[PDB]
């Protein structure tokens, strides 16, 4: 918990701008503004799986 | 991992690469055929996958001669090969005897062809079961064959999905003595029993066999008849 | 993988590993390039002496199939010799049955079908070769073709077959190919072969240059490379 | 459980557990009924048919429907509209199906 | 293992025949709550040969067929449905061959 | 590929999010991100390096 | 404790009975298994059915 | 022959549009050798086209069941199975058309003899759903539940070749409405029925609005009742029953019970089509409970003259025999005092101290009696 | 399932065989998109190219293959199977012209190609030609035709037609598009083909990438379009 060190934000990574935006849309928005996901009336997604080479 | 392939028997049972071919036949499209007193009626169940497909291109009910109808329940590309074989063979009979070939003789020779293909061991057998019928010498006939090379003779039978349910209905509803039209009615009934409900002039395709000869009916008379036939 | 044995079976993702393994077999073979000009086609092969046991003029990968058509093979050598014989046989049949020179597209299609038929069946392997086809005609101009181990045969302006397949066409495409005659393209191919792999992994190489076009009046032959000696007096100036 | 392999036959006995009940995969009409149930909560632009995706076999599990609906709904959240079009289901089919598919119409 | 000085009496096990299926039916059905008025030999001739514990399932699910119609008495039509319930063991022809 | 289908279903893990290898513009982007604080001169054909990058 | 004990109040998953879409076999079968011995166990006992323990 | 097959339909259509009862009935009795002549396949079409479109002309009770009896006579004369079952279904529908007490069920006991053995599973519920109607008509609630469950386990084998899903959904709403427990799902069933009632079923969509908006008033959201009579397709399918829905919707929107009574009795002939008027008098009632609660607390603020029967609204010549009826019949410990004001409700429920001891003494006297045997026996 | 490791062409349990339905994505190793359109007395093919190279030519890359003077076709999948199937179709059309005295109808050729693929499928020990062929043609008394040939040997033929990699989406768009009963006055057809590929791919690109194959009942000769008229149609649909 405490042992997160410092880092540079998501401008440091790149070339994979689909997943960046998509993870933001699936995580940050149903925790900052849940009413966008309640006005529709659809349960937010819970778990996200990153995979690849 | 055995049988594998076509050259050996099982330790006790039967031929697995015939049983699986029958399984693929039973996983085929539904169809029904009824032998009446005066004619024999064949009918199929032909749903296009999309609304793009055309219904004047591929034809399930297929004549072999001017008095012999023949349908299947299985795989079309093999169906065409064995039909073309039956065409050429019936023409060879008409070369030799100058007389239209009887349906029992067709079943003999087509069954010999299919049994030759089940002979060991390099090709697979057909995924095709047939329904052969015709009005030869007054009495009409109805002959169902199978990929194993055998054959039968039915009063009424079915092949495809839920053929057991169609067979229980044909056991229940059908009987010995009907007309051509009544056979058409109960054939469309047993086809609509197991098909999807959206059934038009195009989803079915019906050929009959009068004593006047084979007849492959049109969507005009189909929609004349099947427009809420019961 | 596994699933890689026979050439008739497919994979659970749908490709043939025998074709792929036959493709990357030619990757280990020597570098062979080709490029045409506005009135001719030039071949050039980086060829290597083993250590001291060769003779400089043996087993030349620059074949010559027809009067105006010859190969610039790379890969397994004897398989290339056999395929060259099939090409000679086909050109002979066309000359016999039609009375004039074979057009290069038709020849390439027949050879591509031969390659493809040797990819089809299971008793034989796919070929381990990749080669060039150049030609010239006064009514057709210059045509330069290219045949993979699978049988996909189509045309280029320039090519490379060998290790430095990418690393040659990196700078082949900065050549102003249309406005130049092939006599300039001779020392062009010389500098292209000479830049890649001077001394790095191996010890010594040797240059051959095949040559067809308008200057030879439809003939296809090796240059008199010793005449005008285009490589080394430019190679010693291409190291800086 | 899900796995009926790592169970002692001394457990599946008369008196202990008499019935053997599975939950098999649905078929074409059960998926239509499941769609009719689940899609009643979203706002559903009513000239978008979903039966034409039940025409795509087979191989839908029951847990996948609501995740497809979530993909469609959160894509409509990205659309900033409460309205469920067909392209939402296009992206949902293309995302939550999840190899394989072509499908078929050969040999029936 | 089947050396004759090691194993002596290899005793076959038959499939239950018509009267044998009848007796199996009478045992596995005698202790239930039947309808006043019943036949058993018809049911015994419905089966072309079951196992031992299939007839028990026939009887108990015929009792289930009685209770789904809110009854405790078991008519013949409960058996007419239970025979068809167990019938899904074997069906499936266009397999005569043999 | 070696996960349990007990874990592979949605509900627990809703959307499979796949990352793959960079394309040409993507290789350009990562290369110029790393090539920022590196002491060099104005000579760098990034297209050459990304071209040999495969 | 039964780990709290029996959930005691209102910690249901809060799922309606018609919310399960199109399961005649499953809902009817398990209804016979569990939900019918909740009520008609005194119809079970007089026949001699022995409805299952689990 | 076949040219006369369409001519039977032509002249029978004339007899149904402009012709009269005995003429088309004579035509049904006239074409009886004609069916013997023509091919028996389209015979069922002829039977349907004459019988159904004659019984859907006019209520003439000397001919409906009489021609049904004629169909029984000929169906048991020629003796075919596939044709007589439609006659069976039409006859039990005609028996339901006067809500017949037993003979409809006696006919359904013959319908169960035929259909459950055969294959046509939709033709089963084609009368079983009618039995689910008639067990509401006699209010046999669990057997109608069983019939609906049979319909639900029936209809998952059949695609939709007639319209049958919407009728099932509507009467599913009926059985969910006899419960009076769940209303939102029942409203969903009526709405799905209504989706199946678009422009092809007007005699059912004329009361589908009635059922769904009676349910939404039963759901007690008159805002959405107003917004859905403001719905576009309800305005497509409007009439006078929508005036009933709007007036009772406003009456429950503002709880003016006089508005409720007045607008309710204005449309009594259309109020008959909801035999659940217990909903209406229970909105009256289940509002009047808290009305008497807010008019039972003001009794200690300033009560007026006749503390028991002049406090309420007092509408239209003694609005009581309801309040006093709910002290008589029902209770809230609301004992009457004509001279207090508050009509005092006070009580002491826990007095179990004497209760459980009395229950002990009841059994202790029995234990003394059962010891008296030992007592009188061990001496002599 | 498998289980049997599906090596040769045999029947697997329940009930299928896996070689041909692995060959169904041998088309999908092509990386290409093909669209056929039949609305009225013309018929339109469109298919892109994938040319990254400046050293590679442009004329020899065409997958529109003229079979006969009144029959053209287009290919996807791997190129060698495609070209072999094309030479077989050419040879058998020539055999028809030799034997029967007249120009072959487009259907019979599809039947013969399907029979060849079935014979390569029926007997084992030969790789079963993983390429899909789409045909077009004009027939007298029938107007235009479009047919599709499988590697599976299942020929079929119909109005709006597409095969390749991305054609579940293309068939979805043509289900949503050929449902309205509009006429198809040949620029309607060009516009629908270009825009349906331009919605599947969503690139909206130069006239140098797609090849357009057309045949029309005013000149039954098969015809390949030129860069200028492709640009003319492209800016004509540009609104």
Image (cartoon, coloured by chain):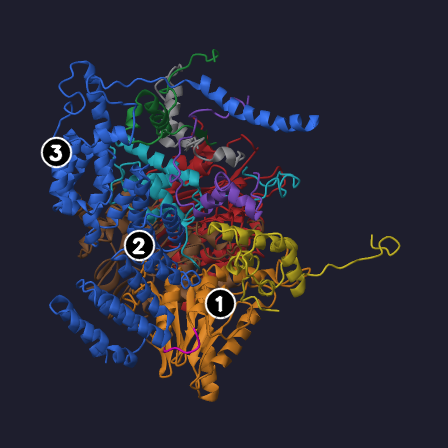
Chain colours: A green, B orange, C red, D cyan, E yellow, G purple, H blue, I brown
Which label's residue is closer to the chain start, 2 or 3? Answer: 2
Residue linked to disc 1: B129
Q: Nearer the viewer, mark 1 or mark 2?
A: 2
Q: Residue at x 57, y 47 (%)?
A: G49
Which label sits on residue H164?
A: 2
- Name the image quarter holding the C terminus of chain H: top right
The Cα–Cα distance between marks 1 and 2, rounded to whole angstroms, is 36 Å
In the rendered image, the vertical position of residue H352 relative to residue I184, given as above or below: above
Q: Nearer the viewer, mark 1 or mark 3?
A: 3
Q: Which chain is home to disc 1?
A: B
In the rendered image, the vertical position of residue A25 relative to residue B11, given as above or below: above
- Residues tagged by mark 1 and mark 2 found on one chain of the structure: no
Image mark count: 3
Q: Which chain is home to disc 3?
A: H
Query: Which of the two residues, H203 or B74, is positioned nearer the viewer here?
Result: H203
Question: In the rendered structure, are the residues bearing label 1 and label 2 in contact, judged by CB atoms less than 8 Å apart?
Answer: no
- In which quarter of the view is residue I101 placed? bottom left
Label 2 Cα crowd, 10 Å radius (few <14 / some 14-19 / many 20+): some
Q: Residue at x 46, y 17 (%)?
A: H353
In the rendered image, the vertical position of residue H339 relative to residue B46, given as above or below: above
Residue linked to disc 3: H259
Query: Which of the two residues, E34 or H119, is positioned nearer the viewer here?
Result: E34
In the rendered image, the vertical position of residue F39 relative to residue I101, given as above or below: above
The Cα–Cα distance between marks 2 and 3, rounded to whole angstroms, is 39 Å
> Was residue F10 drawn as part of the magenta stretch in this picture?
no
Residue I44, image x, y percentages: 26, 56
Q: Main secondary structure of the magenta part?
A: loop
Circle 3 sits in a helix, a strand or a loop, which is it? Answer: helix
Query: Which of the two residues, B191 or H304, is positioned nearer the viewer here?
Result: H304
Question: In the rendered structure, are the residues bearing label 1 and label 3 in contact, judged by CB atoms less than 8 Å apart?
Answer: no
First to last magenta residue range: B175-179
> Was residue B177 drawn as part of the magenta stretch in this picture?
yes
């Amino acid at each position: 918990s405490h042992e997160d060190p410092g880092n540079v934000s998501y401008s440091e990574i790149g070339g994979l701008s689909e997943q960046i935006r998509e993870l933001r849309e699936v995580i940050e928005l149903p925790l900052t503004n849940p009413e966008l996901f309640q006005r529709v009336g659809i349960i937010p997604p819970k778990g996200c799986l990153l995979y690849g080479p | 991992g055995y049988s594998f392939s076509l050259t050996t028997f099982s330790p006790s049972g039967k031929l697995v690469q015939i049983e699986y071919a029958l399984a693929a036949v039973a996983g085929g499209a539904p169809s029904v055929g009824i032998k009446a007193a005066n004619g024999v009626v064949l009918a199929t169940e032909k749903k296009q996958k999309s609304i793009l497909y055309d219904e004047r291109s591929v034809h399930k009910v297929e004549p072999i001669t001017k008095h012999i109808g023949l349908v299947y329940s299985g795989m079309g590309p093999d169906y065409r090969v064995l039909v073309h074989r039956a065409r050429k063979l019936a023409q060879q009979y008409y070369l030799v005897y100058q007389e239209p070939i009887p349906t029992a003789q067709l079943v003999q020779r087509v069954a010999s062809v299919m049994q030759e293909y089940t002979q060991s061991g390099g090709v697979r057998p057909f995924g095709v079961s047939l329904l052969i019928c015709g009005w030869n010498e007054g009495r009409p006939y109805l002959f169902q064959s199978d990929p194993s090379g055998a054959y039968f003779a039915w009063k009424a039978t079915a092949m495809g999905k839920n053929y057991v349910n169609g067979k229980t209905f044909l056991e229940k509803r059908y009987n010995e003595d009907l007309e051509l039209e009544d056979a058409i009615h109960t054939a469309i009934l047993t086809l609509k029993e197991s098909f999807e409900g959206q059934m038009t002039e195009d989803n079915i395709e019906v050929g009959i066999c009068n004593e006047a000869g084979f007849r492959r009916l049109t969507p005009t008379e189909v929609k004349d008849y099947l427009a809420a036939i019961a | 993988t596994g699933y890689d044995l026979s050439a008739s079976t497919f994979s659970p993702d749908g490709r043939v590993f025998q074709v792929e393994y036959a493709m990357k077999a030619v990757e280990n073979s020597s570098t062979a390039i080709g490029i045409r000009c506005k009135d001719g086609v030039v071949f050039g092969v980086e060829k290597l002496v083993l250590s001291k046991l060769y003779e400089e003029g043996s087993n030349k990968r620059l074949f010559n199939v027809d009067r105006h058509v010859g190969m610039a093979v790379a890969g397994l050598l004897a398989d290339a010799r056999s395929l060259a014989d099939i090409a000679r046989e086909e050109a002979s049949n066309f000359r016999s049955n039609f009375g004039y020179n074979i057009p290069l597209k038709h020849l390439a299609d027949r050879v591509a079908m031969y390659v493809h038929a040797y990819t089809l069946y299971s008793a034989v392997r796919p070929f381990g070769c990749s080669f060039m086809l150049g030609s010239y005609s006064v009514n057709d101009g210059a045509q330069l073709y290219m045949i993979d181990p699978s049988g996909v045969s189509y045309g280029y302006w320039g090519c490379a077959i060998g290790k430095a397949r990418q690393a040659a066409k990196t700078e082949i495409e900065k050549l102003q190919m249309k406005e130049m005659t092939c006599r300039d393209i001779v020392k062009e191919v010389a500098k292209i072969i000479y830049i890649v792999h001077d001394e790095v992994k191996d010890k010594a190489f040797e240059l051959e240059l095949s040559w067809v076009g308008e200057l030879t009046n439809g003939r296809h032959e090796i240059v008199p490379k010793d005449i005008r000696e285009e490589a080394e007096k430019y190679a010693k100036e291409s190291l800086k | 459980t899900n796995r009926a392999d790592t169970l002692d036959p001394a457990l599946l006995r008369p008196g202990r557990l008499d019935r053997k009940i599975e939950f098999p995969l649905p078929d074409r009409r059960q998926k239509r009924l499941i769609f009719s149930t689940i899609t009643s909560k979203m706002n559903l632009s009513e000239e978008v048919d979903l039966e034409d995706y039940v025409a795509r076999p087979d191989k839908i599990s029951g847990a996948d429907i609501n995740s497809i609906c979530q993909e469609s709904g959160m894509l409509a959240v990205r659309e900033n509209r409460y309205i469920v079009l067909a392209k939402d289901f296009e992206k949902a089919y293309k995302t939550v199906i999840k190899k394989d598919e072509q499908e078929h119409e050969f040999y029936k | 293992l089947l050396r004759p000085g090691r194993i002596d009496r290899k005793i076959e096990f038959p499939p239950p025949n018509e009267e044998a299926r009848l007796d199996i039916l009478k045992i596995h059905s005698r202790k239930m709550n039947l309808t006043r008025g019943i036949n058993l030999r018809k049911i015994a001739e419905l089966m072309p040969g079951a196992s031992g514990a299939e007839v028990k399932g026939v009887c108990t699910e015929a009792g289930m067929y009685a209770l789904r119609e809110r009854r405790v008495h078991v008519t013949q039509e409960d058996f007419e449905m239970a025979v068809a319930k167990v019938m899904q063991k074997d069906s499936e022809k266009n397999m005569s061959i043999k | 590929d070696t996960l349990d289908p007990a874990l592979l279903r949605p509900g627990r893990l809703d959307r499979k999010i796949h990352i793959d290898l960079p394309n040409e513009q993507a290789r350009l982007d990562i290369l110029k991100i790393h090539a920022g604080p590196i002491t060099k001169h104005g000579e760098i054909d990034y297209e050459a390096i990304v071209k040999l990058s495969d | 404790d039964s780990s709290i004990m029996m959930l005691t109040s209102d910690q249901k998953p809060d799922v309606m009975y018609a919310d399960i879409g199109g399961m005649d076999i499953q809902k009817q079968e398990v209804r016979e298994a569990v939900e019918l011995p909740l009520t008609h166990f005194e119809l079970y006992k007089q026949i001699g059915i022995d409805p299952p323990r689990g | 022959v076949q040219v006369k097959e369409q001519s039977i339909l032509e002249l029978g259509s004339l007899l149904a549009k402009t012709g009269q009862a005995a003429e088309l009935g004579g035509l049904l009795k006239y074409v009886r050798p004609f069916l013997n002549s023509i091919s028996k396949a389209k015979a069922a079409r002829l039977v349907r086209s004459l019988l159904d479109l004659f019984l859907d002309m006019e209520a003439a009770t000397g001919q409906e069941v009489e021609l049904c009896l004629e169909c029984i006579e000929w169906a048991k004369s020629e003796k075919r199975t596939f044709l007589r079952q439609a006659l069976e279904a039409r006859l039990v529908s005609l028996y339901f058309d006067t809500k017949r007490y037993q003979e409809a069920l006696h006919l359904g006991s013959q319908l169960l003899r035929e259909l459950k053995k055969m294959d046509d599973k939709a033709l089963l519920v084609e009368v079983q759903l009618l039995e689910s109607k008639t067990y509401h008509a006699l209010s046999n609630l669990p057997k109608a539940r069983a019939a609906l469950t049979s319909a639900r386990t029936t209809a998952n084998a059949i695609y939709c070749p007639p319209k049958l899903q919407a009728t099932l959904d509507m009467q599913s709403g009926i059985i969910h409405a006899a419960e009076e427990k769940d209303w939102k799902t029942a409203y969903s069933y009526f709405y799905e029925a209504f989706e199946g009632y678009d422009s092809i079923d007007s005699p059912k969509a004329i009361t589908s609005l009635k059922y769904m908006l009676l349910c939404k008033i039963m759901l007690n959201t008159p805002e959405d009742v107003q917004a859905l009579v403001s719905g576009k397709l309800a305005l497509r399918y409007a009439g006078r029953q929508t005036e009933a829905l709007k007036c009772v919707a406003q009456a429950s929107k503002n709880r003016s019970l006089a508005d409720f009574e007045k607008a309710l009795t204005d449309y009594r002939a259309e109020l008959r089509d909801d035999p659940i008027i217990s909903t209406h008098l229970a909105k009256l009632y289940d509002n009047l409970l808290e009305q008497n609660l807010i008019r039972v607390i003001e009794p200690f603020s300033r009560v007026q003259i006749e503390h028991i029967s002049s406090l309420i609204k007092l509408s239209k010549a003694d609005v009581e025999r309801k309040l006093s009826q709910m002290i008589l019949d029902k209770k809230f410990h609301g004992i009457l005092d004509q001279g207090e004001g508050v009509l005092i409700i006070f009580d002491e429920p826990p007095v179990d101290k004497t209760y459980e001891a009395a229950l002990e003494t009841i059994q202790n006297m029995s234990k003394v009696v059962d010891s008296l045997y030992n007592k009188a026996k061990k001496l002599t | 399932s498998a289980g049997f490791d599906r090596h040769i062409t045999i029947f697997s349990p329940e009930g299928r065989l896996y070689q041909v339905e692995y060959a169904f994505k041998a088309i999908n190793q092509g990386g290409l998109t093909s669209v056929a359109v039949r609305g009225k007395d013309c018929a339109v093919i469109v298919t892109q190219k994938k040319v990254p190279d400046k050293l590679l030519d442009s004329s020899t890359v065409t997958h529109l293959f003229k079979i006969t003077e009144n029959i053209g076709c287009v290919m996807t999948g791997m190129t060698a199977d495609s070209r072999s199937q094309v030479q077989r179709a050419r040879y058998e059309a020539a055999n028809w012209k030799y034997k029967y005295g007249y120009e072959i109808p487009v259907d019979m050729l599809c039947k013969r190609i399907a029979d060849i693929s079935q014979v390569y499928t029926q007997n084992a020990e030969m790789r079963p030609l993983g390429c899909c062929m789409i045909l077009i043609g004009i027939d007298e008394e029938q107007g235009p035709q479009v047919y599709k040939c499988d590697p599976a040997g299942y020929y079929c033929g119909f109005k709006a037609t597409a095969a390749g990699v991305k054609q579940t989406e293309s068939t979805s768009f043509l289900e949503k598009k050929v449902k309205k009963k509009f006429d198809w006055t040949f620029e309607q057809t060009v516009e629908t083909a270009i825009t349906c590929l331009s919605t599947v791919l969503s690139i909206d690109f130069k006239p140098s990438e797609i090849e357009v194959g057309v045949v029309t009942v005013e000149n039954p000769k098969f015809r390949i379009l030129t860069e200028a008229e492709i640009d003319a149609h492209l800016v004509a649909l540009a609104e």
